[PDB]
Amino acid sequence: QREYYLREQMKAIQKELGGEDGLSDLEALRKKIEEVGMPEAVKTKALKELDRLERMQQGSPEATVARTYLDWLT
Amino acid sequence: QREYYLREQMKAIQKELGGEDGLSDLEALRKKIEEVGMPEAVKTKALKELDRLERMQQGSPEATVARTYLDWLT
Amino acid sequence: RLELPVIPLRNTVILPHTTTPVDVGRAKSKRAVEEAMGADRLIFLVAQRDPEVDDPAPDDLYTWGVQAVVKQAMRLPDGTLQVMVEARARAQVTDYIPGPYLRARGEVFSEIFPIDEAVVRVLVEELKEAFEKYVANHKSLRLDRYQLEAVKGTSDPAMLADTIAYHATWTVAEKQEILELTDLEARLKKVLGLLSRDLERFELDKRVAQRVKEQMDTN
Amino acid sequence: MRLPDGTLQVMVEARARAQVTDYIPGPYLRARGEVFSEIFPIDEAVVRVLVEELKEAFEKYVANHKSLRLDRY
Image (cartoon, rainbow over all chains, first blue to last red; front, top):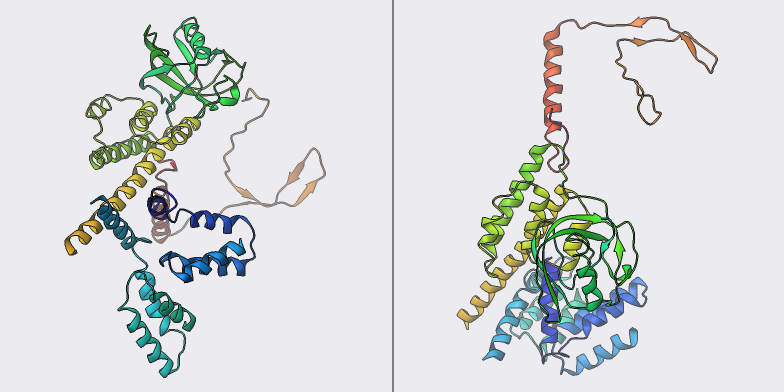
């Protein structure tokens, strides 16, 4: 109920960063990681690269390649 | 004013990130520096890099490289 | 119970012995209302799922259905037949003619008295105390003061658990799950666990409220 | 008595444990037994201390069930 309610609020946020499309897409990418595949090593590596991608600003040029990598993995 | 309000309640959420913030995960990093190993010069080097890191911000254009460097050290 | 004309719920679930007005908009359902009047003011109410298969069928539905006595019959021709029903008891479904209008029976009553009546009255009193605290904890929704005065005057704990869960706002799935199991103590612990987890939500609310206070005062 | 489902309930209470010499083949069964082995309690003070200990243990086991309803009578 803790992580649930807080995930509720954070997806409300990733919605509300512009009403939609804010982040709004990387919990869908969490689901996309969870659905297709994976072996456990690439699973852990993709979740660590996601955790690298999360905290930072979206306009940075490191977040450009750290998004394209998670898009080529899944 | 409501944008101001959004920023307020968003940052309070991020203070409440998992349970509360990954501050708990941040002093977990503080522990994880001096658990495994390490040689003394590398140890003081990493602690001074962390001291350089703690002056930076919640973004950031250059704190991502610093804490990625500490992750690769640990 | 004996193939009453099934009239669909179009909203949240009726619980036993709840003073409930029922909207009946679709004409497919409306002649099932007039021959529920032809069925001695008793409907084997079988709820369906939301946004709804508005072809009447057993396919629509929820396999645990409530019995309900009509109190009054409103001739209100506003595209939706208004009927007030006080409920009786949940039931397990035993047949289906489809519809409009369906024919479907049931079996059981919500009269259940588990043994060791001490544990009955104790978990009843602890659900009572959970409700008395929760209604004090959630006047953020400003719950009703007759929902304290009418829950005093209760003598069958089954409809007590049903009236308390009905007064408490939940999902459709939770109310249907309360109507699936027939037992007292399970529905008691059900309402109790739901109140406790909403209290934990409320605690998270107080927590982030203090966080916002911190941010505003600091800045 | 006979139950209405064709299942014979028999209410038994054991009075003595018993030894066995030999079995006669069956069905049906007949059997003979050596002795009615009985030992009566002597010095009931410390034995009664152990009875009070087992009474405390069963009184502690009765109060285990709050949503499970072990019998209190």
